[PDB]
Image (cartoon, rainbow, N blue to C red; front, side):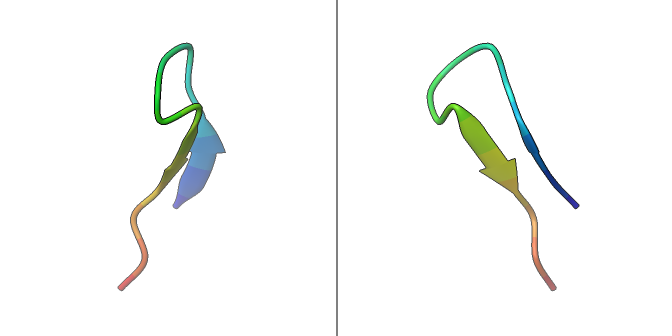
Length: 16
């Protein structure tokens, strides 16, 4: 899953 977050990295992503 990949989604933005209130902190750097502003963009989250945990690919397989």
